[PDB]
Length: 336
Image 1 (cartoon, rainbow, N blue to C red):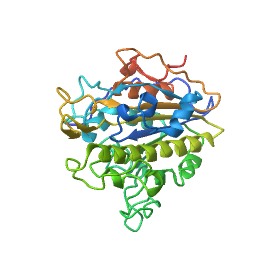
Image 2: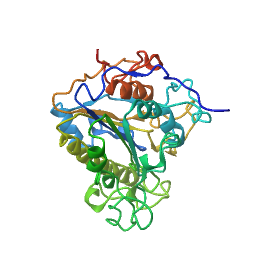
Image 3: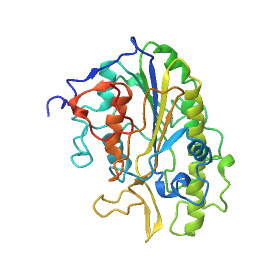
C-alpha cells in the first residue's frame, strides 16, 4: 500500500502562535471509564468529586453521555485521532491514513505523547520517537515515570505523567503545544491495582481478577475507586494548566470506551459494536478552558456527541482550517 493516505493537504493554520497568544492543549485519553458511573452524569456515588465542583461552579463543561466509536482500546484510540468517522473507520487500515496528530505536527504544533496504558496504537508512528515517552515503567526499568513505587504492585501512576512537564513547554514556548496523556485509568479486570491507598474509600473492594466470583458490588467499588484516582489526576492536570498564564489553555478528557460491570453477565469490554451493551459505548467527556479563553463550548447536537468530534475539536483548538474538517460536530466552535 505504497505510502500514506492524505486528508489535510489544504490544512492551513488561520492564526499562528507568532501573531497571537500561544495555545497549550492537554488531551487526556481516558481508559475504560464509563459515563454511567460518572457522578456528573447522575451517578449516586461521588466518583468525580473535584470535577463535580468544577462543573457545579461552571469551570469545566460536561457533555453528558458521549458515544464511543468502539469497545476496545486498539480500535478506539486510532479512530479518536482519525479523520474517518466511526462509520467509515477501519481499524486494520488506520495506519495508512494521516491523522490529526500528523497534521498538527506537520503544521508546527509541538506534540508530546506520554503513555501509561500501552501505546499510541499507531498514532505516533510517523512522528519522531522522542515525542513518544514511555510511562508504564520506571527508569531503571527503562521508563520515565517516577511515581511507581507507591503501591504493593509497583504500578506506575498517571500522575507521574505530570512530572517535569514544564520542560517540554519551555522548549516550545514560541509555538502551540499539544500534550497527549494516555491514561491507565479503569483498566480491568484488576481494578484494585489501578489506584493507591488514598483512593480506597468505597469498601469493601474486590481484590481479585475473577470478577465473576466476587459479588458485583465489591467489583463496582473497585471500579469506582479507580474513578476517584482519575478525578484527582484530572484535577492535578487542570491545576498544572492553570499555572500556565502566558498561554490560552484547554483540557479535553475522553475515555476510549466504557465498561460492563456484570450487566446481564457481561464483564469487561471489547464486544462488537453491532450488539455491544451500551455501557461499553457510553463514555464521559469533560472540557476545561483557561482564564479569558477565546473558545466557546459548541452546542450539543441531540443525536449527541461522539468520538468523531475529537479531531475537528483539536483542529479548531489550534485554528487549523481544512475541508477534511469543513464543519462537522466538534466540542469547540471554530474561531473566525
